[PDB]
Amino acid sequence: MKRTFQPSVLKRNRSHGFRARMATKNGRQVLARRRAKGRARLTVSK
Amino acid sequence: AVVKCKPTSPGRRHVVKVVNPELHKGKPFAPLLEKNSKSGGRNNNGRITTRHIGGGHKQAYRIVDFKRNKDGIPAVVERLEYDPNRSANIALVLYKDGERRYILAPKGLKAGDQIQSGVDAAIKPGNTLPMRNIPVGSTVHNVEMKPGKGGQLARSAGTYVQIVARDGAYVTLRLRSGEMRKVEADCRATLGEVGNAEHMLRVLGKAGAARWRGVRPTVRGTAMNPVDHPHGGGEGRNFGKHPVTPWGVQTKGKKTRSNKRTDKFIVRRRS
RNA sequence: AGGACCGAACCGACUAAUGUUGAAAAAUUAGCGGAUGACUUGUGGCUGGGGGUGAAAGGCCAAUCAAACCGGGAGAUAGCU
RNA sequence: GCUCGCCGGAAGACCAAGGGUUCCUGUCCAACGUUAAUCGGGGCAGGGUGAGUCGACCCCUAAGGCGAGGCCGAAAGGCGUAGUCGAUGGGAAACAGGUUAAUAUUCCUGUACUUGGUGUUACUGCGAAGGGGGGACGGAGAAGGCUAUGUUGGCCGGGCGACGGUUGUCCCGGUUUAAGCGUGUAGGCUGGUUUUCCAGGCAAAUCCGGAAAAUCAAGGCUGAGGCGUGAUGACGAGGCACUACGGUGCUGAAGCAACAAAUGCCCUGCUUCCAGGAAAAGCCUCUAAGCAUCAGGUAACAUCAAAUCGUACCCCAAACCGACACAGGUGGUCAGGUAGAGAAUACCAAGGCGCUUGAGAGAACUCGGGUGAAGGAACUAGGCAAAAUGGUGCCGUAACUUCGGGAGAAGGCACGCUGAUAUGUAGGUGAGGUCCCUCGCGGAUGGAGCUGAAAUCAGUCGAAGAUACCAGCUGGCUGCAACUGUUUAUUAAAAACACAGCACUGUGCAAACACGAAAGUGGACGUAUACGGUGUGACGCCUGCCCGGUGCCGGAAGGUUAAUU
RNA sequence: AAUUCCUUGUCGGGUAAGUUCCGACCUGCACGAAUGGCGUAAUGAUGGCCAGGCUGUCUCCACCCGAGACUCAGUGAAAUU
């Protein structure tokens, strides 16, 4: 059975990558929230 | 020519084809071709704004000259070509100076026929002149609505308009819809009728033929549940309400013209 | 020539048995339908929640859909246990 | 190590995606492995990924994204121009052999090729953010010519048989060699060459397009494969000396022909059809502004440069997606033998595996199968399930029908093996020889050799010859839907949805309509033979009466009637 | 009748026996003409019905071949309470 998660690095970076987050005001707020929480990994970049 | 396919299988029984041997059996004129990507009926927001559009065969757009402003230069028809972008056929015409262009094919235009445009052109099919010089009561097509912007009326397979009167700077025309409309007596029109009259006689014959044209299936609405359509719902086939669009407009006589900007060029709207 | 015929790949899911703390949160086995087309498939792209998409079942929208998910208003309110 | 069994259009081989050291070596067995474990994709340590030619980067663009100004919007922000990004597409070049425990078209040997920089020499009109050409494109079908590859013969080496025979028409193995360069063939496309002229290609143009003459027919382009060279080489079954029986030096014979033959190549071709089939750059040309004893351009030679990143390993799976070492899912490439129409199926080759608890016993019962006296649907909601039919050829085939069908209707007959016709026929393939020739990869004749159905006649074995796997049950009446299709991923596949066809109605283009506070976008680069909405649902015969109600479309006197005053 | 409550309507066909099926009848509870009427060849993993063939579906089960169940060694769950 085909499962929901079909990995693709290009699609992963384009959808949730660091530059994608920085491209919009709401995405930048996501980074600010994660920085405030002290996340070790800000995004899925690497 | 209208030819009925033999019923060798269900799907060909009711197929009626319109075969025109005069059409060029080769590639079109490359310099006058352009890319034409399909939209699926979706606008720049990505939302479906027109339903039942999608798929179909890939098509290349032919740059058809609807203005016909090359006055004083005879042109000879080279061949008749099939145009996927419209119901009418197009004609490749070569001017005396060496320029080639695409025009809508009139009724009786063949290869080697001579055409011209301007105020001194002869009154014969395929020629384009301002309606001021066109004799009243004649049949024309590819009619301009504002001088110099290219024809917009009577461009379909076998359409045409008739000049009924010419009072002053305006000429009254009877359109295929039956509307009596008047336009400035400076708009260019082409003599004759667009020649593909048999185009209306074709019978697709099967669902797939419509899909080739790029038409997606239409879901009625009485089978849609109330959440999706005003007609939806009911145990069985009920439909106990006045016919209506999606979004709630009547569809059975309710007039929707609310322009009011022109309101002078209409005389005998229709019917 | 064909939304033509028989039939593998491929795409489907009509019947039965098994399984039902399963090998598997829908599969296996034996049959079954389509199989040049309104076909199928890889990669990338677009449409966002009273919105999308829907050959229309209220189907589908990340194992969740008669209004997704996450956080917040929030210790909603509960004449009921 | 010897047997046995299993896969072999994979359960083999090579990749992308994804993973990220799982790769190799040594060492360890606590935990992990559904058991033990000396073993492991486990622990620990070390080692391992070598590129001008492969890929990425890079140049070019598709859908689409972003978007200087700009337009629009309470703010956030939306759209979009010039531009700039974006492969799943276009764009220069390397092959064979050898080699490591683990990498190689990357290292080594041999032999090649591509794009740039610089310098010398010779001859010269060079120049683009512009013009033109090219790149550049669909589906289906049909052969013809080929190769991959296979079979047989010949050749070379070895063998003479655990049990009757086996020096022969016998047995086993091998019989391999690339890119590049030269030749330009089967075949495809197109008439060339010179001169003059021109409202076109935003200006220009010798280029493209167009026009008018003169002269010749042979000009050019494209093109698989073959052949030659590459190659006095490499490889090569086996030997000969060391040989820790783990392997290394040296040597190493034959290395041909015929036939068959692709879904691969010629072919981005040809034929045909309608639903009419990307873009841009590289590349080839044209000139403008400009520079011309310069600069630049072309050719030859020499020299230099070609960076950077990826390269291990799994990749239909124990390493990816499924919480698992999970009967699931996962795109591309390679495609041997016998039988066969076949990539079905059976048995096999190369290669890879026996699926990480076993050992006994031979109760009920359950699961998956085999057979069955007599009967033969009496079972049951229902022939559920099972059984049965099953191939090729010939004969034969009803009602009805839209004349296509129904139809493989139904039904009947023949199928093995051996010999002969014919020491292998019809057919296919085609050597030598001869002749012709614009003397070449040519044409005609020619038939050796090879390959090879089908049929008839006769004989013959068995219970059974389409013997296995494989492989339609058939017919009669009737409801519904015309049909092929679509649907409740995960209890409903249907009479439901679509459908071609039909009708009503809206819509004159800045269209109706739709998404948007708006700009704008779709509709459509369409224009009433068009487009939207609604109902009906092939086709045939038809579709009657009613406008009081509700809606819709018109109308005009009169009544009533908002803000405002 | 995919529509008929009364109802297994009545008659005929098929069966030894037919609330189903087929053909007529018309007393249409409560068909009816594009939310179409009536026909219709072909088509259908569609509904109903009848035949030939076929059979362990059944009368009525018997035997056999394998995988479990049972015993030994190793590992070692669950719902519930």
Image (cartoon, coloured by chain):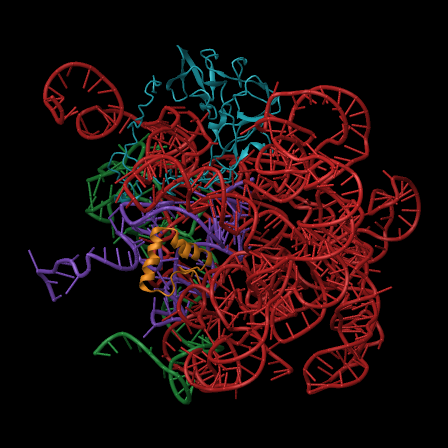
Chain colours: A orange, B cyan, C purple, D red, E green
**Does residue E3 sit above or below C30 in this rendering?**
above
**Does residue B262 sit above or below C59 in this rendering?**
above
Q: Quadrant of the N terminus of chain B?
A: top right
In the image, B41 versus D147, the foreground residue is B41
**Does residue A11 sit above or below D537 in this rendering?**
below
In the image, B161 versus D450, the foreground residue is B161
Instruction: Give how far across and how far down residue D163 sits, in percent.
Output: 74, 84
User: Residue, x 34% and y 51% (percent of image)?
Assistant: A25
Looking at the image, residue D374 sits to the left or right of residue C56; the answer is right
Q: Is residue B170 visible?
A: yes
In the image, B129 versus D405, the foreground residue is B129
Instruction: Give how far across and how far down residue E49 sits, in percent.
Output: 36, 52
Q: Where is residue D111, by image quadrant?
A: bottom right
Q: Where is residue E32, by image quadrant?
A: top left
Q: Quadrant of the C terminus of chain B?
A: top left
**Does residue D254 sit above or below D25 in this rendering?**
above
In the image, D381 versus C14, the foreground residue is C14
Looking at the image, residue C33 sits to the left or right of residue B225; the answer is right
Instruction: Give how far across and how far down residue B263 sits, in percent.
Output: 32, 20
Instruction: Give how far across and how far down residue D527 sits, in percent.
Output: 43, 26
